Every structure is written in C-alpha cells, then in structure tokens.
Image (spheres, helix red, strand yellow):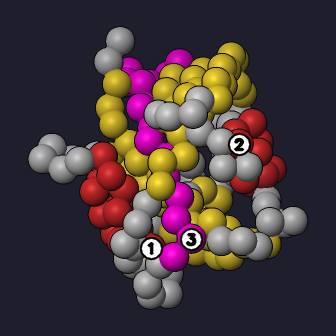
Amino acid sequence: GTSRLYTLVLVLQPERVLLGMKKRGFGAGRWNGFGGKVQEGETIEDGAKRELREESGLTVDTLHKVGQIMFEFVGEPELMDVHIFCTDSVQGTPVESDEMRPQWFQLDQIPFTDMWPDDSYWFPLLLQKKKFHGYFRFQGPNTILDYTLREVDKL
C-alpha cells in the first residue's frame, strides 16, 4: 500500500479552538481543523500554512508540530499520512467558503460527536501539548476498526 501526505492545522488558543464545518467532500457534515494535500515542491510545514490560508483565509507566522497519524480507510486505495500542527496566533478573520464554515468553540464545548471519531482519542494529547504518532483504521466514516497512539518527546 501507498500513502499521500496531508496537513491538518488547529488554531488552539488558551480557552478556545477554531474549527471548520465541512460542507462538501472529505468529512462533510463534521467540524475539523484546516488541511489538505501537501504539494510537490513545498515542505510539509509550508503546505500546512498554505492550506490554512486557502481554507480559512487566516495567515500564520509560526506553526508547532502536534503529531502525525496514518489513516487507513478500507474502501480507499491510498493511506493518508497526516501531519498535524497548531498555533495560538493568526492574522485575519476566518472566511466562510463553499468548502466550509468556521466557528470558535470554547474548550468546554468541543463538539466531539460531530467531529471525526479519532479526535476523541488524540485531542487529550493535543490539549496537554504532548506529541504523538498514531494509526487509525476505518470502515466508513463512523467505525474505527483498530487504532494505535504512541506519545513521543520529538516527532
């Protein structure tokens, strides 16, 4: 099996987190961070900044590495190698698109039942600032067949 590179960015401040409700395509109807395919000719980190800009309108100076997860969906031919990043400081207001609608959530109102089910497993790592490598195997959007999470000091 082969894998494609993706990024996912979470704008995570001391008491709130920015999410986008996907309108179309992958994860439609769920809140998620901002991300997409890494392109030829850009670093993973630059891809993460570009996707944040493209998806939300926001610009960022500094991203920090949160973790990395390999996703396997049984009905898809490629694995998804997802590099996850966070930041607490952005410039601009997020802009609604045909692809998504942005919204801030207080950290006591994170809507896990309307997010990808894997978020329930690794968000506690995210919120404690603990880096990790992970793997999730899915049958469709709702069923995790198997998963592994391993906390690390350095990615």
Left or right relative to 28: residue 58: left
Q: Is residue 62 above or below residue 116?
A: below
Residue at (35, 63) in percent of width and height: 49
Tell me how many marks there are: 3
Which residue sits at x=52%, y=65%? Answer: 87
| Labels 2 & 1 near each other (Cβ < 8 A) | no
**Res. 150 visible in picture:** yes
Q: Tell which of 15 and 7 is nearer to you.
A: 15
User: Does label 2 or label 3 sit earlier along the sequence?
Assistant: 3
Where residue 140 sits in the image (x, y, percent)?
62, 29
Question: Dot 2: within a 10 Å radius of its alpha carbon, few (fewer than 14), some, or many (20 or more) residues?
Answer: some
Q: Is residue 107 left or right of residue 154?
A: right
Q: Quadrant of residue 144?
A: top right
| Residue position for label 2 | 125
Residue furthest to the right: 108
Neighbour tally class for label 3: few under 14, some 14-19, many 20 plus, Cα within 10 Å = some
Magenta span of residues: 73-89
Marking on residue 56? 1
Residue 153, how many percent across, how many down? 57, 33
Marks 3 and 1, the one that precedes in the sequence: 1
Where 147 sits versus 28, above or below? above
Q: Residue at x 66, y 49 (%)?
A: 129
Marks 2/3: CA–CA distance: 16 Å
Which of pointers 2 and 1 indicates the residue nearer the eye? 2
Give the spatial CA distance, label 2 vs label 1: 24 Å
* Mark 2 residue type: Leu
